[PDB]
Image (cartoon, rainbow over all chains, first blue to last red):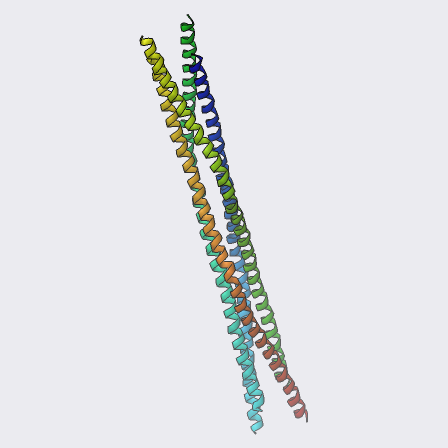
Length: 95
Length: 95
Length: 95
Length: 95
C-alpha cells in the first residue's frame, strides 16, 4: 500500500524537476531575445545619430560648393577677359 | 603673338576638363553616401518594426505564462490531495 | 601692360583657392564614407559573433530539451502505472 | 474509490495541457529567435556586399584623382609659362 504513496511521491518529484527545467529553458530563450533586442536598439540609435547629423553636413556642404562654383565662375571670366585683352594687343601690334 | 592666345586657350580647356572631372568625382562620392544612408534607414526602420511588435508579443506571452502557472498549481494541488487521500485509505486499511 | 600680368596672377590665385577648396570638400566626403564603412563593419562583426554563438546555444538547448522530454515520458508512465494499480485495488475491494 | 481514479485522470489531463502549452510557448520563442537571426544575417550579408564593392570603388577613384592632379599640374605650369612670356614681352616693349 506504500507502493501507491511512493509512486505519487515520484510523480511529484518528476513534475517538479520537469517544471524547473522548463523554466530554465524558457528563461534562457527570453534572455537571448532580450539581448538581441538590445543590440538592435543600439544599432538603430546609431543610425538615427548619423542620419540626423547628415542634414547639418549638407548645410555646410552647400555653403562650400557655392563658394567653389563662384570661384570657377571667376576663373572662367578671368581667362576670358585675358584672352580678349590679348586679342586686342595683338591687333594693336598688327598695326 | 598667337603663342599667348593659344596658351590661354589651353589654360581654358585644362581648367574646364579638370572642373568637369572633379564634378564627376564629387558626384560619385555623394551618391555612395546617399545609398549607404538609405540602407541604414531601411535597417533602422526594420529594427523599429521588430521592437514595436515585441510589446504585443509580451502581452500574449504574459497571458500564456499565467495560464501555464495556474496549470502547474492545479497539478501540484491534485497530486497532493491524491497523496493525502491515499494516506487516509492506507490507515483505514491498517484497521 | 602690367594689366595682363596682374590678371594672370589673379587667375593663378583663383585656381589655387578653388583647388584647395575642392580638395577640402572631397576629403570631407571621403571621411564620411570611411566612418560609415567602419560602423557597418563593426555591426557586421557583432552579427557574426551572435550567429556563431547560436550553434553552441542550440547544442545546449538540445541536451536540455531531451532531458525535458524524458521527464515528461516518466511522468506520463508513472501516472498511468498509478491509475492501473488503482484500478487493480478497486476491484480487489469490489471483492 | 472512483474518487482516486478520477483524481488521477485529472492529474493526467492537467499535466497534458500544461505540457502542450509550454511547448507552444517554447516554440514561439524559438521562432522569434530564428526570425531575428535571419534578419541579422541578411543585414550582415548586405554590409559584406558594400565593403567588398568599396575596394573596386577605390581603384577607380585613384585613377580619376590621379588624372585630376595631372590636370591641375598642367594648369599651373601653363599659367606660369604664360606669366613668364608676358614678363618677356613687357620688357621687349620697355624697349
